């Protein structure tokens, strides 16, 4: 009965996401692939969900869920194809679940994948109050010969940054600690939006721009900047014996990160190892294609810029250097 | 560090499940398919997990997780290909998580799918004590022309039952209520095993036998008996205007169900609408193939029998009739 109200309630959102490969959860492979390989992953949104629960605002958290999954697929060159979610809760609140699922559908549309199935589970005793937990699962497709595996990254490659929408879905344990110690007023305005708005802003989805970029340029590696922040994730594009030399003149941290550091008495050292600091993706490619790639990304709605280059590194040194 | 102990700890279990299609989470389609269609699903284990947590016994619950997912795929004719899990907890207990994941690997091997990825998430504040929640996701493959869609079911078809291992992963809310009201001693012996053992017995996986059966016989429909028990799930094989006429002489409920009914003061009416009552799958096929199908299922390690037939039904009547 509750799950019946919900099923009817979301069928619109689900149908919105349908792509022609979907049959009748059945899905054909897109016809363009000659040697398709499936690329899959699962993710949750983490402590960001705790903030959404604190704020009782559930309409965008599904976008973060889809984003986490799909932005990890694009790093290998995969085109998202379909998506499923598992939603667990103590007592099913149909409005809440419908809001979450609708935001999942919003994300799926921006990622170009169909929401084809899912599960809503009641686990009384496991979740307190109005809490729920949601897991996402995505399957994408890549042409076998075109997998981006990082083998092509060279010393001398340029590094492009693609701008983030805010903290995305990482660092939210520190966010919540900052908010609780400072007893922060989430209604405070900063640059025309409330602090709560800035912090719940959904993760940017990089599929439309990413797929176009990969099609038009020689992309050597991509890193999706997630747990461990800017500092930990940049090295995923680096061969052994190299470093990312970051041009510190090339961007300013988005103001929400500056606010978090000030409000929270946080070191820059910790900030860089927790938050994306404005960088959602970093891309390695030849220097002579970097400006064209940047223009393409911008044309597809991203913020993008040349943030650095890959240099030879000695045995001792840090793999990320800001200068 | 905790997630590092765990990753090393499970890599053996994961490698055990590898199939040749896995590359390097990357997976090719099996070569035999001419027009492959992907079939996918997500599931959790439900309140059975609460029993495993009550009993602090985590080594088989992953089998139930895989079983729930894969036994739903086989109903459409799909061959499980790969599997991913999302494990969420308040504080990561590496031994617990490793036990769960190893049991997932056990299930994957029996289902013939590779465990190719997953996520372990810490959500402090969301889960109390040692609680965790685990979601499963599976992708299988079916030849487009060979999808089992139920269109072939006929009045006059035989119905075969495939025996369950116990309650599988459904009815465990009622199980726990029975145990709590009766203050049942889970160490009590029944037919050579403890009550706790009977109730945690992992769900039977029907892939090896199922795939062979579909290959060798004209299977019209299959229903995996899950939520709502024997009574609610049998009608999934039925066209409009038909009923399942069940031969009540053809089996005896496994003793654990009789124990649950007696201990719990439960009506037969409720039992049939909650538990599988010994039937894990029901299969519709031509009568002239039923005996051969039964022998095949038995040769592949199942318990199986002809449990009834599909008859014409009048407007008013129940779709399941035991006589
Ligand atoms: N949270 C969800 N997201 C997407 N689809 C769902 C969700 N919950 C249920 N469904 C779909 O609705 C139908 C009934 O769901 P269930 O029997 O609970 O898995 C199935 O086809 C599901 O795939
Ligand atoms: N519960 C799990 N089951 C299977 N694989 C996992 C699990 N947790 C982590 N992994 C794998 O271990 C690596 C590190 O995990 P993570 O970065 O937490 O997703 C990834 O390749 C995961 O796919």
Image (cartoon, coloured by chain):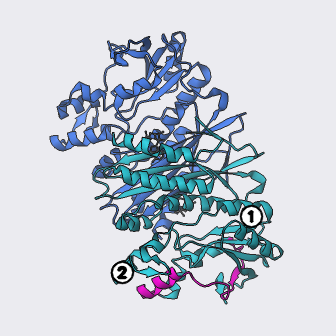
Chain colours: A cyan, B blue
Query: Which is nearer the eye, A14 or B195?
Result: A14
Q: Residue at x 40, y 28 (%)?
A: B233
* B245 sits to left or right of A300: left
The reply to whether residue B187 is visible in this rendering is: no
The reply to whether residue A305 is visible in this rendering is: yes
Which residue does the numbered mark 1 point to in the structure image?
A213
Whether residue A186 appears in magenta in the rendering, the answer is: no
Decide: marks 1, 2 in contact (CB < 8 A)?
no
> What residue range appears in magenta?
A237-266
Whether residue A242 appears in magenta in the rendering, the answer is: yes
Q: Look at the picture and state if A127 lies above or below A237.
A: above
Q: Secondary structure at mark 2?
A: loop
* Sooner in the amino-acid sequence: mark 1 or mark 2: 2
Q: Which mark is residue B28?
A: none
Badge 2 crowding class, 10 Å Cα cut-off, few under 14, some 14 to 19, many 20 or more, is: some
Q: Residue at x 64, y 75 (%)?
A: A234
Give the x, y percent position of residue A132: 37, 56
What chain letter is assigned to the residue under label 1? A
Q: CA distance from mark 1 to mark 2?
A: 40 Å
Q: Given the current orientation, which residue lies at the most extreme right position?
A: A288
Which residue does the numbered mark 2 point to in the structure image?
A184
Q: Secondary structure at mark 1?
A: helix
What chain letter is assigned to the residue under label 2? A
Q: Residue at x 36, y 13 (%)?
A: B247
Give the x, y percent position of residue B302: 46, 26
């Amino acid at each position: 009965d509750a799950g019946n109200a919900l099923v009817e309630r979301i069928k619109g959102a689900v149908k919105r996401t349908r792509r022609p490969e979907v049959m009748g959860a059945l899905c054909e492979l897109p016809t363009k692939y000659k040697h398709p390989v499936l690329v899959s992953g699962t993710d949750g949104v983490g402590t960001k969900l705790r903030l959404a629960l604190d704020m009782k605002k559930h309409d965008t958290i599904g976008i973060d869920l889809v984003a986490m999954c799909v932005n990890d697929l694009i790093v290998q060159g995969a085109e998202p194809l379909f998506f499923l979610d598992y939603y667990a809760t103590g007592k099913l609140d149909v409005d809440t679940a419908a809001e979450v699922i609708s935001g999942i559908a919003d994300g799926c549309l921006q990622a170009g994948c169909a929401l084809i199935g899912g599960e809503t589970a009641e686990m009384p005793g496991m979740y307190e109050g109005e809490d729920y937990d949601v897991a996402g699962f995505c399957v994408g497709v890549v042409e076998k010969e075109e997998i981006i595996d990082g083998s092509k990254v060279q010393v001398g490659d340029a590094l492009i940054a693609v701008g983030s929408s805010g903290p995305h879905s990482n660092g939210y344990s520190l966010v919540r600690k900052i908010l609780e110690v400072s007893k922060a007023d989430k209604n405070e305005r900063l640059a025309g939006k409330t602090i709560g708005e800035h912090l719940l802003a959904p993760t940017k989805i990089y599929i439309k721009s990413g797929l176009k970029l990969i099609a038009e340029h020689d992309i050597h590696a991509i890193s999706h900047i997630t747990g461990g922040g800017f500092w930990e994730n940049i090295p995923r594009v680096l061969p052994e014996g190299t470093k990312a030399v970051i041009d510190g003149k090339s961007w300013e941290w988005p103001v929400i990160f500056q606010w978090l550091q000030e409000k929270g008495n946080v070191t820059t050292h910790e900030m860089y190892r927790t938050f994306n600091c404005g960088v959602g993706l970093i891309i390695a490619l030849p220097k002579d294609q970097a400006n064209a790639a940047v223009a393409l990304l911008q044309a597809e709605g991203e913020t993008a810029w040349v943030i650095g280059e890959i240099a030879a590194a000695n045995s001792n040194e840090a793999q990320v250097e800001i200068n």
